[PDB]
Figure 1 (tube, rainbow over the protein chains, first blue to last red):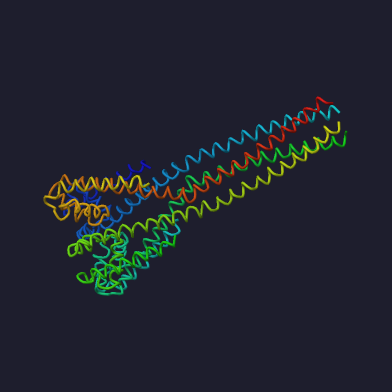
Figure 2 (cartoon, each protein chain N blue to C red):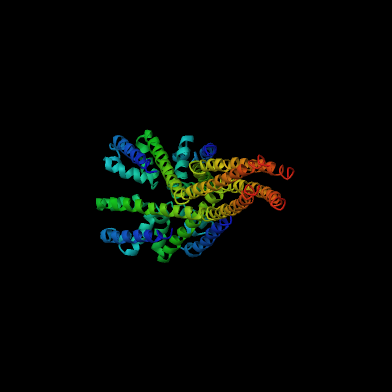
Length: 136
Length: 136
Length: 136
Length: 136
């Protein structure tokens, strides 16, 4: 799960230098610094005035910015979906299906100890009986 | 799961030509092209200034646009809910309940091999014994 | 699950007449009609300019409107959470844990048919043997 | 699950007095009272004009407010994720994996009653047979 939290903080990083490279020119409030894009893209990630506030006016200057915003939201919120699910799995198979996946791993092999002793008891009886057809 | 990703990209398409047909007239910034609606509806799908920015002013010109926006959000975000769930199911029954659904499919039939051999051993003993009530 | 889709469409209704009763006076664009509140509250439920657009200006006229908006969002989005979960449960215990809850209900009782026949075979052997201690 | 609903309503509280302490000075509409921050932070938690509306203008006065907003959203929406998951777990292991975790706790021990009676029957037979090699 936390092996993707690295990936997310890489995409966040990659796209922050992208926007600083592109829009630092004409949108210096949103993309002037690296640290200003780190904020803007967080705001863009949270989908609060992402388009009407940021994307639309940025797309007005460069139409090659349309994809930068769309692709960012697509990849960003998608690797959160992979991350949100990475907690539902690691949580529902840890508190429920990791304790049951061992209690039924034990209750199954606690009757292989029952069946395989009982088997021996029947063989110890096949030995006592088949030695009495050779004795009568 | 990805059999609905086609459906979503059909609803996205269907509604994009709808808005271009309707609003290309008076809202050319948002619905002028097919490609402008493809953007606007993505923005409307992400619920960022969807109403106050897009729907409200569009509903001011045509009140028959109220339903276009509401219905779009309802169907769109609903087939994402069907898609979001389509990953939680295909993920929690693949990494947990597809490996366990085979290890308990094997552990169950590894004792039918135990019970049905043991049965034979008892019949081989019923054969040795019921041939000794006919021998005494 | 769909037994709460009724409840949600009741809260939606209840609060729509509430807002039309209260704010139809001074906010006639948002709450003038029943059908205008049905839209506004849908927009409020989707959390798009819910506060800065609707609540804040409505709270400026009446401070007894603060709770109307907060309580609405709390109850509304909470019975969606009960509804969103009502599909995750009804879907993950239907496609996975309703077919397995019957295949293991059958595989369990397919060996009670094995154990209880084998038992009889041993009793049919206790009958053949304990009638040979009375015969020797 | 509801043991974190207390924690959330503590973070909500902690950060509300924080913002009233800091921003009551120059942003009295958003942070003037304790009760105004309780609203603003709810609006900030719902990510509706959180940055462009609240954070950005507040960051314009104090750049030491950037972290207050980011950290709030991070911790707040994260302990909702822990809370949202705390219902998926407590619901999917209660309606499905708490009734099955008892029906298979009973079906397992209803055949230990079978195997351990059958064992006795074989021993009662080893007693009858091994007393007939000492009798012939």
